[PDB]
Image (tube, coloured by chain):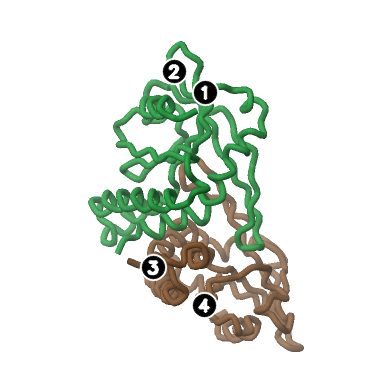
Chain colours: A brown, B green
Amino acid sequence: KNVADGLAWSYYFGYLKFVLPELEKQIEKTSKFRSKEKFVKKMFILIPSNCFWDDKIPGSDYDPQNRITFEGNTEPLEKTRGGVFLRHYKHSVYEIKDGENEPWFCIMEYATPLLTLYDMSVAQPGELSREERDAQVVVFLRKLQDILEGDRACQGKYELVTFSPDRDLADVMLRKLKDSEL
Amino acid sequence: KNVADGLAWSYYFGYLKFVLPELEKQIEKTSKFRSKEKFVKKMFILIPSNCFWDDKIPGSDYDPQNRITFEGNTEPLEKTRGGVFLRHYKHSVYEIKDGENEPWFCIMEYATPLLTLYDMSVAQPGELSREERDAQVVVFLRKLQDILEGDRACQGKYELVTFSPDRDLADVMLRKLKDSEL
């Protein structure tokens, strides 16, 4: 009985399945983003091991050197799931310093279902102990991997980023941006 | 290994936990709603056994006699979960005919996580057969019940409504409105 399984399936069917194939095209609707070099177009999905975040990424405890900057949002995508309810999806673009070189642009987002694991561990410790939460993050990660890898339309459109609350996200992101295919 | 468990926990922590205690107060912000008699203030959470809906409730296949009418929305409640993202929650008010009597007002909403069960059964039939989906609806119902019944702040603020695609929702709702405490 893994609570993480329902969380991963819902994250996929209720969100990623339709935003990931369209992300690059949505980005390309903005001239500045068409003009920009070093703009990796994958969604970097952030999975902190403690299931927690409480603020904007720039200047946060994960950005101690202040090398991450909010640039702007992508053009919203429209989607109807209920057949009745229209929703607008957009993503945040961040600038990441690369020393004296041209800075990178990238798309970063926390995996929002992890808040449910966090909320559960604090409000219902009897249902989910701290150690059980740690284990469910790994389960969530592996299941989300299986799901996304099984969808050809999502291939090359995302990257899962796992890290400890002590890591420097700017350092983590620079390495991943440099290793990306673009 | 039940996918429904994560769906129920996330439906609660990401939504119901904070909208259910405030629902009556939100409704009371509208004079028309303060003035209206026969307005039951509980959220009626709709759980169709086939996990599916594709249109507005009024005049739908669930309202064959056209006795349900959209009245308006409640005043939005704002909430911040991530610490970063402000969201607005509001609910639909419906009028339900009661013969020649004063009609009822009520709050009705489909349990939106059931869409994930439906989407899964169609796109990944190998992961969730039709019969396994039927069973996960029951798991979802029982788990959501356990969760809500364990939260004193949610007591008396909701009612779960399970029904088959052949039932008349107007008939189902009239009986439940009459049996409500108000």
Residue flagged by tag 2: what amino acid is it? Asp
Residue flagged by tag 1: what amino acid is it? Lys
**Classed neighbour count for the residue bearing mark 3: other residues with Cα under 10 Å, few (<14), some (14–19), many (≥20):** some
Q: Residue at x 65, y 49 (%)?
A: B78
Indicate the chain on which mark 1 is placed: B
Dot 3: element: helix
Indicate the chain on which mark 2 is placed: B
Whether discs 2 and 3 lie on one chain: the answer is no
Residue flagged by tag 3: what amino acid is it? Ile
Q: Which residue is mark 4?
A: A49
Residue flagged by tag 4: what amino acid is it? Ser
Alpha-carbon distance for marks 2 and 3? 48 Å
Alpha-carbon distance for marks 4 and 3? 20 Å
Alpha-carbon distance for marks 2 and 1? 10 Å
**Classed neighbour count for the residue bearing mark 4: other residues with Cα under 10 Å, few (<14), some (14–19), many (≥20):** some
Q: Which residue is mark 3?
A: A147
Counting from the top left corner in percent of width and height, residue B57 is at 45, 32
Mark number, residue B136: none
Q: Which residue is mark 2?
A: B98
Q: Residue at x 49, y 67 (%)?
A: A121
Disc nearest the viewer among 2 and 1:
1
